[PDB]
Image: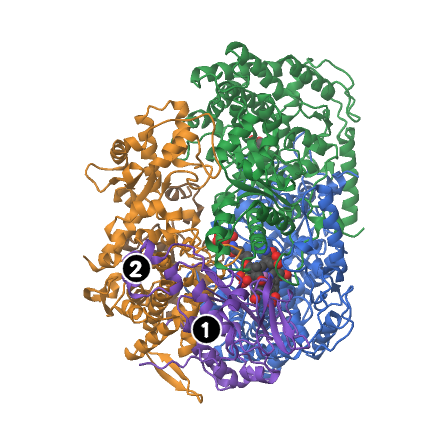
Chain colours: A orange, B brown, C green, D blue, E purple
Amino acid sequence: SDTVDIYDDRGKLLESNVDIMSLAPTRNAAIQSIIMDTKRSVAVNLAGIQGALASGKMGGKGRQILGRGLNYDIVGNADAIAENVKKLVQVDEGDDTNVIKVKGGKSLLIQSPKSRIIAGADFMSATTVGAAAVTQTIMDMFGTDPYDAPIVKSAVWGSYPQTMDLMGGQVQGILSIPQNNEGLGFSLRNIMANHVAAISNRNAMNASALSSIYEQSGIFEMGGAVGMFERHQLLGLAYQGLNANNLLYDIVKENGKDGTIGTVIESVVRRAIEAGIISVDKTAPSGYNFYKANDVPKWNACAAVGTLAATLVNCGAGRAAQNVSSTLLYFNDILEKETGLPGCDYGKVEGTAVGFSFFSHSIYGGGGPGVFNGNHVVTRHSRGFAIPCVCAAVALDAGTQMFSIESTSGLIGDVFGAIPEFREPIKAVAGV
Amino acid sequence: NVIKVKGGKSLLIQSPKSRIIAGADFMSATTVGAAAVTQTIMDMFGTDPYDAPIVKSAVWGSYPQTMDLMGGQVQGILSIPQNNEGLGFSLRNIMA
Amino acid sequence: AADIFSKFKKDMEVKFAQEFGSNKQTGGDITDKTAKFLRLGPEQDPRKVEMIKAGKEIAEKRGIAFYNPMMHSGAPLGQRAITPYTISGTDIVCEPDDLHYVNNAAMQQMWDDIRRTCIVGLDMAHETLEKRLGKEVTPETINHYLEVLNHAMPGAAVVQEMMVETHPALVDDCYVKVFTGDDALADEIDKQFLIDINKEFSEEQAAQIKASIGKTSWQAIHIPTIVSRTTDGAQTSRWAAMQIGMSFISAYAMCAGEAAVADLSFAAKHAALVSMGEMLPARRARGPNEPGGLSFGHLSDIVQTSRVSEDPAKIALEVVGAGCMLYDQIWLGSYMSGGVGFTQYATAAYTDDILDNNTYYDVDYINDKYNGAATVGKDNKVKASLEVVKDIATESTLYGIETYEKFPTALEDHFGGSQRATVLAAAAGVACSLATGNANAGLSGWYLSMYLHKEAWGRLGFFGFDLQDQCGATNVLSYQGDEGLPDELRGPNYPNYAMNVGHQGGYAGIAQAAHSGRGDAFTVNPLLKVCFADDLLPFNFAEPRREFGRGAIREFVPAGERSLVIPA
Amino acid sequence: AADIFSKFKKDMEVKFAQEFGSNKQTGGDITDKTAKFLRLGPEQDPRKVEMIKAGKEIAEKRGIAFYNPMMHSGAPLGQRAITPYTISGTDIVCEPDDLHYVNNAAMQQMWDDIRRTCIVGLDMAHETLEKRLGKEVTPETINHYLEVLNHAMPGAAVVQEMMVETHPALVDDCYVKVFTGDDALADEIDKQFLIDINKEFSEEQAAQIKASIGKTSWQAIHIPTIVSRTTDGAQTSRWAAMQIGMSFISAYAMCAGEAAVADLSFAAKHAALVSMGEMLPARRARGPNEPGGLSFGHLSDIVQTSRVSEDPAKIALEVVGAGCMLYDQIWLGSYMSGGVGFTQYATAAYTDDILDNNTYYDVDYINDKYNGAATVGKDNKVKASLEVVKDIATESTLYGIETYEKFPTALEDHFGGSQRATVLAAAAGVACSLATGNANAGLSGWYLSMYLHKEAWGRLGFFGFDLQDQCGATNVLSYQGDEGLPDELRGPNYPNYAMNVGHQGGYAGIAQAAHSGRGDAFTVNPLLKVCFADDLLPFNFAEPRREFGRGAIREFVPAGERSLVIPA
Amino acid sequence: AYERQYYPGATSVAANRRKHMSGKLEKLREISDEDLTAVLGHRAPGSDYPSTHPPLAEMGEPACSTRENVAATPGAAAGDRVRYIQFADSMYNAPATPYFRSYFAAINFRGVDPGTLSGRQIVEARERDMEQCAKVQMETEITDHALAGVRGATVHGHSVRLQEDGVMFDMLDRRRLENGTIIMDKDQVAIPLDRKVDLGKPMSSEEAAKRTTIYRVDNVAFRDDAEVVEWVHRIFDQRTKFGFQPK
Ligand code: F43
Ligand SMILES: C[C@@H](OP(=O)(O)O)[C@H](NC(=O)CCCCCCS)C(=O)O
Ligand SMILES: O=S(=O)(O)CCS
Ligand SMILES: O=S(=O)(O)CCS
């Protein structure tokens, strides 16, 4: 019996006395709905297909097949295409298939019925059936000669199956392909930070909330929340992810005007002492107080909140995404030096942040904060407590990045940002 | 559903449907199953923390150095998702 | 066509009717159905004698058994005649063993030249400097950057104190050039760094290339062969990115390690990278820039014959030769298997002018029946149909089969059914591609050839030769997810094609043929076409077949040797 | 220990207090905190002068810019003194540049010898012959099989007519030997094929190996270096399997291609195959037998020092040296990045006897405080605990830090914090492993060293050095799925370890140390330990550090060169 | 109300570390705004700050609680480029050590992106914000300009033996001792300045030893600060235990 009150992104009470166990991906209907919708949905770029058909530019960077041009008005027929795609994507008449025209006909949202996910081993049916539906629809609508069928197919599918993905195709989802998983249970962790920030409409706390839902759904699928580790991860999800007891919001607010990474540490330690979560274990000759954690999972959750609060404060002040890597490192490093207690994830947020800083400031790989995700070799290491900060940091950026949200995730934000549970995940999990 | 089979030489571990519903694929059956067995052995036999790696790898094998539980003691009917040649191929990776 | 038929017959004379080494094949009519088999063993061949002696001495020296032809079951090699191969289109007569990739530096270098190469855009990197640092990028700063880059790329330092570096004498094949669809910028690039699109290509082809890529600028990077050989293909894009990053840091006076540098990294490694090929699935796990990921269009564009010839058949045939070598000898014959391997599965397509004969017969047939459809042009082509494919592929295959039957020497040459199948189907497929300008019409012709072949002789290829060929006709125009694909985008990882010899080089030629018949500048990627339009590379990609011959006669100098640091 | 301390000081004298080339470092006290910096540039170093000359001439010859030290920002390399490195445990004084893997044939050959090697069981194959064909397998048929195999494996024919083959002179490093835990069979094997476990190992170590593997028989296959270089690691098991299959077909008069052959294939490629390392995930996609898949236990077993030395510290230190070279210079420094790379990140752990000094000090400390726990033995070890780790690791790190502080030459030597971190943590980790016989107690000591280091100097390593080190202590005894693992089974793909220099070689030494302290025959795999117990391999795996020195002085002869087919 | 304690230890080194972390640093010298801009090398002295995007007030922002509750810095508000100041600090008792410069920045300045390495420490921030932080680092005891150097590239020196005049080696010779005072006549990437910058007289080795945040066996040994060694031991123990089981 650990309960929290859930507050939204604006610090308003949503629901009181929520058992944290009810927030588990394995029990929570809203979280499972977000997961199902993420699994069953893809975006199709109709304008991209039309351009690819006309130019022969399909199948990857630099690719062009000369002399095979097809001039089909895909976008001008977007409504008829959406209708026929739904007929092909749906399994039964009147089921939960949803095909929606987006951006004046430039793209489609194709949501497979949940039956395709229920009957599938993973989530790729959304992509394959979505792509097949579009391919068949174009073939029929524009009366493609059989010897031109390969051109229509690859306008949609790109270089698949020569490539393992639809490289240079026109179908995208929030997830990747299963073969890109580093580990077992990592599919829901392979979600680009820019995607989450795009979907959140650049709302920092809703971005970290949605990211937390994905990350912890991953940790649960990884078998990293079994036994005592379930309470451990759920306290983190509740407090860091879902603004439990308004702790996240309040710490950010009281540090918002003049605060730093350093002042957030004062807020975190003061509140942890007030709550009785930590107390002085021993005082050294210098007067330095070594603390002890009376509830270790709860202390971890305090540190998780502080890590995100420091991100919102430090990235917020700079309106700069890049500050997140140092924030995660130094909030936890300085917290340990302030208290004698381990930082969030017992070093693993700090550790993740060390490599994350390096790989967002060096020649060797990585990139800006937005390219990272829970399946990324650089940022996988912490158990869900780092990437939510990265998503919030990206949401707060005012325009310093080359690989911005629009650059990498324009289609995703436009196609998926209108889904209520996705844009307002705290409210969704709370039950409004 | 967890059933003892072969006079205790092996177990069937069936995760609740909720783990599959809340998951992107099917590996939660393996990871949760292995985690449950690992935790159970750690507790039942009072393993010292400095011997925990040995108990863990008795179950998980070379994971996560290897992508699979190579030399572990957990198997299912399916493989791991990364062994898929194509998209939608997971249920096709079942040896005859 | 007459001239190629004469080359074919000449090759049969050289191979079978005048003795090679001491094989005592001193006469005979190349149309004779009978022969005498002298049971001379491997000693009839001077290369085999050299190998026997080497194996004997090395076994004695190292103290464990080694090469010994008497370990062959029943009898040693060469109980019939061991006879040479002439590289098609040339007078280079080769020792058969000299065409094994292990024994041929030209073949190994061709792969190394592809493996160690990647293409990285400049525009995004320049946009990064502009936006984040407020830098002004000019031809002057670019030329300075390029000189810094050509110091750094081989493995040398530009920022830190107390660095060790690669020895220049070991990495002299490493360099970076640039090309750009921006003519105004091209005019300002120091010519030592420039691949000049307007100079290297005809005006029509240069126009197609520049129209395709727009006003964008690209780096053609070739990392050291010695590094490529020590490591793998997935090394290449990483190596390129590291030294691109260092050179931007140095040339533009950035902080040596700031946030903006990470954007350059992502650009170089991912967002502006064009690899030769992509990664492969778990059962044949490999990273980028390995032969399995190399699409048929990409190989067609690496091969430079399209740029220097106006003969659409010649252009397709060189791509077939390069492809059969790479895909069958090195890729399927080593990477995916190994041992003795698949030398002659491949040589069947690029030696003794047999494939060339069938192909040029087809060109004349097409031109005479379809108003010159096999001559270069975009508007003189026949509409792709089952009708046209059936006509061309049937005529092609019947002629090729009858040629094997009228010349018993040709049949004994291509002694394996797989070899004959590759030749007949490559000719029929290239022919259908040339006539239609549709690469998948070419694929249809390939598969129909196989079906006719099978019923003609009551045999086809080896045990599993026609897995893809029986799946073939039906998957040509399928639009199902893992079935449909234009041939230009197909490659060794296209599911049906993933295993078997005698095909992949043919499909590459079929892809090229659809575009060479039209006079197209490229088959699928202009960036690769321009990248390899560069004579500084040790392998001459304009004439791959002749290069294999240069290798066979030990006149090819490879890169990456370690002589400098080895004792004498 | 006193002898090693004297060696360390001699190294500092050679490096800093007597001239190297023309660096004019003609005198000095190695404890002096100050120095004069002469701003001589690269010309002070004779190897650098050689490189400059080559760079200039090659640039002139090839017509595009090349190596040019003046392209370095601000000033050319060597504004302070360029000074040599002495290979630890030896008197081999090296040019710094000669320790870059590109310039060092010994380093390249060590990787090739690992990459081109796999182990394949014989028992399954023999059971297949017995069950499916009713064949009787005897010592006679096995010895005949092995002679056939050693003809076939380098790339030569045993069944078909008209085969081309690899030239024996190009593939002389290729061979197959066998070993077996069945003493009765070992007595019957032709000694030219045998790796004798009873001969090569001490009686205790041989007993451990034979008890581990039982009465099973294995093939140690080493495919041609020239093939490994042309292709990749994933080539190796395929190459071995092809020629094993051919040799079984020939030696046992099977049908050359029947259903039973397919069982031999699956046995050789999968069921009875032991690879050096397994495949890697998509972002760093590579097949088997690449450095990233090579577990720390497997490297510890490839290195042969455990077999020939009774000094547990020496055994661990040789593994550290081999690992730092392979994992940092070739793997992380090339495969995973490239360019100038990470030579000195690695050399810090195998030159100038600084790591050795810290380690041997620890051994004396442990023996003194813990009743000789660091001496070889299974029952004299201290129970692994936080208390013992804190004691040994803190003492180790404090001594190492004080040595860097008392000898400013040592600090300037290991000028990068990462280098010092690798040395201090390796010593502390190796010490904890030696004392406890628990490799993960060794890991705990490694991470505690890093933590003490950081607070001592207000700095640690490079920007992202301690990603794994801050995740470190907490993941040592974690049993969470992607966190828990004995160090013996950890490797470069263990998630925390997947990126960064300065660690992987240390972890290999820590794995080895836990078992060398016990006198164990192997660290994790007896099959690899026996496989590399073979002096025929070009690289001496018993003395890896010294081998790097032999490479530096250009006295190492590698395999795989192509001079035979290269023109004059 | 919680009073921060910052860092354990009871030596001069620990006391100096708390001074750096808390930002309680003695001002020792002056640098003009234009000279600071000159040594940083991102724009001409006295010129307007370049921008990477329009001012926040011009383009507007998403309305969420964080942007409303967290005040943008002057540099963020202006849309400044993110630029930097980077230091190398000698291990021979330079007042500063890399991690403690980073703690200084993280604790005392808003909207900063500090990075710690062995041979270089960097603060990235919106240019005008960065200059505020830079000024304090240049003027106060956290920097001795003989034992440290502002270096945006080619940083080698922190671990190299000192020159006999007590100045840390610089490959690119950006700053040196001239007439008993430290002169910097190139910017931090070694481009020559129009006007040399007087960075004041260096600390004596004695004063540096008193002001330093680094431990050394021949000044204040790390081994002798029992509280800090115990702190490490407690962090190590707890991290190890909780990784096994967080209880
Ligand atoms: C440009 C970067 C940013 C980045 O992502 N990587 C660099 C540079 C890169 C380049 C430098 C080559 C060149 O000069 O052109 C290479 C060789 C990687 C490559 N591309 O081949 C490298 N680092 Ni670095 N790099 C190294 C080091 C270091 C140490 C050097 C500290 C000192 O006081 O000298 C510092 C990090 C730290 O402070 O801990 C460092 C930083 C940096 N490292 C800073 C430049 C710092 C500067 O301006 O001088 N390296 C080392 O500490 C030792 C190993 C050494 C590597 C070469 C080798 O192993 O032989 C090299 C490894
Ligand atoms: C992070 C990742 O890079 P990307 O972000 O995917 O571009 C990875 N690089 C590395 O980990 C390089 C490590 C070796 C060079 C740095 C050593 S400290 C790789 O290329 O797969
Ligand atoms: O005989 S098989 O068809 O199995 C192999 C052909 S090389
Ligand atoms: O300076 S960085 O730590 O990013 C690279 C060290 S080689």
Residue visible at 43% across and 28% down? C475
| Mark 1 secondary-structure assignment | helix
Answer with the quarter of the image where residue D401 lies: bottom right
Residue D356 in view in this figure: no
Which quarter of the rendering shows the C terminus of chain D? top right
Q: Nearer the viewer, mark 1 or mark 2?
A: 1
Q: Residues within 10 Å of mark 2 (few under 14, many from 20)?
A: many
Residue visible at 47% across and 28% down? A66
Residue A401 in view in this figure: yes
The answer to whether mark 2 is within 8 Å of ligand 2 is no
Which quarter of the rendering shows the N terminus of chain D? bottom right
Q: Same chain for the residues at labels 1 and 2, yes or no?
A: no
Give the percent coordinates (x, y) of residue D194. 69, 53
Give the percent coordinates (x, y) of residue E171. 65, 65
- Residue E103: give its label: 1
Q: Chain of mark 1?
A: E
Looking at the picture, does residue D58 appear above or below residue C377?
Answer: below
Q: What amino acid is found at the position of numbered circle 2 in the picture?
A: Ala
Give the percent coordinates (x, y) of residue A92. 22, 37
Cα distance in 3D space between marks 1 and 2: 28 Å
Give the percent coordinates (x, y) of residue B65. 49, 58
Looking at the picture, does residue A186 appear above or below residue C319?
Answer: below
| Mark 2 secondary-structure assignment | helix
Q: What amino acid is found at the position of numbered circle 1 in the picture?
A: Tyr
Q: Residues within 10 Å of mark 1 (few under 14, many from 20)?
A: many
- Residue A209: give its label: 2
